[PDB]
Image 1 (cartoon, rainbow over the protein chains, first blue to last red):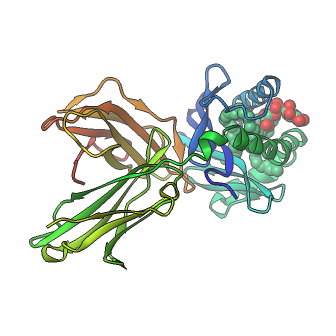
Image 2 (image 1 turned 180 degrees about the horizontal axis):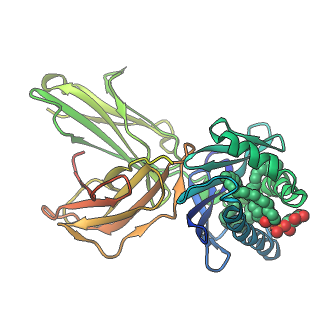
Image 3 (image 1 turned 30 degrees about the horizontal axis):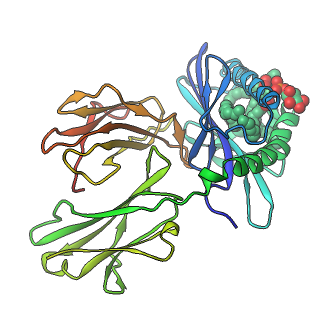
Length: 277
Length: 100
Ligand SMILES: CCCCCCCCCCCCCCCCC(=O)O[C@H](COC(=O)CCCCCCCCCCCCCCC)COP(=O)(O)O[C@@H]1[C@H](O)[C@H](O)[C@@H](O)[C@H](O)[C@H]1O
Ligand SMILES: CCCCCCCCCCCCCCCCCCCCCC
Ligand SMILES: CCCCCCCCCCCC
């Protein structure tokens, strides 16, 4: 019953250039909003917002850092160790993402996915290591192998099913002011690159809005134009978004058309901009 | 070992208005592997003070990054974004089009 992000996750990107050269980049997120950075040299987190620690104490934050710090080092080490055994050709990248999310009703589901060479490799369903089809024999061998480690499994379980949920509620609450704010968008029209002699491309820009959900369409009166092509919702570094909505039209059919924008911050007052003769 | 070329999109945070300070953005995404180099150019000269996001990726695991910098648009001054990536035999330049 609230807006803004409803989930948290940390990501990992580990690049292996050769048998003794590997680097790892990580960060913490609330949906698409980054709230944690990770300084590799000093295995310490970088808190991007005043409330990034959620309701956690400095002592527990330091425990988690230490945990990720040794995991990062150990992960690199074991990958280099089993590289040959797992028949791995350098260079290669391993990606990971783990977190949890709050669903309506109060349930919180956790998740964890790993990738090798940009393709699914594994994931964690109901507390177990599930190899991915694109993971081939490697994925099956790794999962089959990793589950034998009592220690790492118990830690993954705790982080995933006890710490993550507790952390989430704490940051969603601590950062409420920013996460649930409403920023009105600003729209403007422009003439895109002509699709051909006699044609024209109508462009509608919507920017600076937050939260992310938004509705933009080209209209003729109250008739939505089906040819309206949405662009990707792009980010502005200030926690707001940018979006284009285009419409390929004939020189004569331009007049009469308009761009309509709906957004939760508008409170029913849609932005309507008309194309002028 | 897949390789995906980066999608490059350039845009200003606000509508272009010569004189008024704005923000130039270069969003590059859908690429893999992650190693990449991005530069925001001004008339072909790589801009100096440019900020960028820490690496991130989508659900399909392809990486994305936002490169930006506060800037003032003039009637002239052509801005663009330059990308180097294992998928490009040579740098790719995507100019900033105010009407796009
Ligand atoms: C700012 C606040 C922070 C917010 C927190 C929110 C958390 C969100 C989700 C996080 C999920 C974390 C996933 C990865 C973490 C793995 C992990 O912590 O285990 C690591 C193992 O180190 C290795 O030697 C590396 C070998 C390489 C092997 C690793 C492979 C990866 C896993 C594979 C997936 C399949 C498994 C499926 C199982 C469900 C570190 O163990 P540690 O030394 O801390 O010992 C621990 C630690 O001290 C702990 O606290 C103790 O409880 C524990 O007993 C001890 O062993
Ligand atoms: C205090 C928090 C700040 C953020 C720190 C982030 C550092 C890294 C976090 C750990 C990443 C979790 C994902 C694990 C899944 C990867 C396993 C894939 C194995 C495949 C091997 C071929
Ligand atoms: C893809 C190949 C990586 C192999 C990972 C094996 C992990 C072994 C457990 C670590 C011992 C403390």
